[PDB]
Image (cartoon, rainbow, N blue to C red):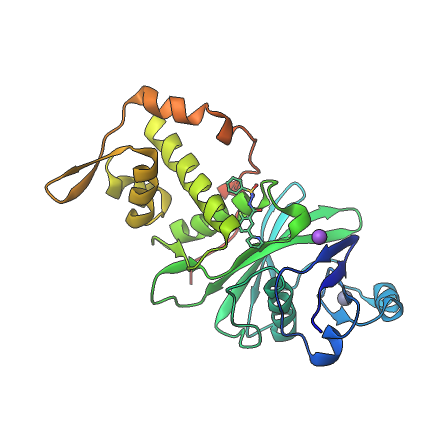
Length: 268
Ligand SMILES: Cc1cc(-c2ccccn2)cc(C(=O)NNS(=O)(=O)c2ccccc2)c1F
Ligand code: NA
Ligand SMILES: [Zn+2]
């Protein structure tokens, strides 16, 4: 029997996939997770006793973003190994294609939290390889189900690209993406590229956004905004065609924005 239900903070959440928690944890009707330190527990009693004891009220690592009650914590896999393993086991409950849970040393983890008077409540995260040969600026990205489709995933996507900008590189998410990750990236790429086209070559868009050119081109192909000429993709759009796509209904939700002013992060 596998873990199929968890209790984290004030949420109960059904699992989507097998996650390799130890055998005795899976057997339980559900797992109980501290929302701050990510310790997983077998019983409501041990969970309740932990809530009385745990002094964590936020992720470990360094708070590299804070604007109002939105916060990002950066957590090195080698410095905080238990915590990151727990994060990975939690994430594999909702990620089919994630394969790495216990070897967390090569990754850094970016934890999105919503803060209130009692603490910084975990919303989701993305991992990132410390040195990615393939140039991927996201390895796995995961919004917990109660927070999905509410702007947090978009926030985390924008954030991964703000880091890629500060590193003076382009990046792309590691593939395959979930069905919901595909739609989220496509929607984000559209948004960003359309806004820049309204406000330019494919290389310019790439440098301005840190989106790779492949991702730009394939997004413009699906928007039908690219011509082909003698082997080169070329941007073919009129200022009104862009505005037609933008003011359409599928971009009308007000984002949680990444404010670069509030991103205290230096590239190493
Ligand atoms: C990258 C990503 C991944 C996942 C995910 C995948 C598997 C398991 C759990 N989570 C969820 C979201 C999410 O929640 N997307 N919705 S969104 O933030 O409102 C939004 C709106 C407009 C453009 C972009 C994003 C997401 F972005
Ligand atoms: Na659920
Ligand atoms: Zn705890």
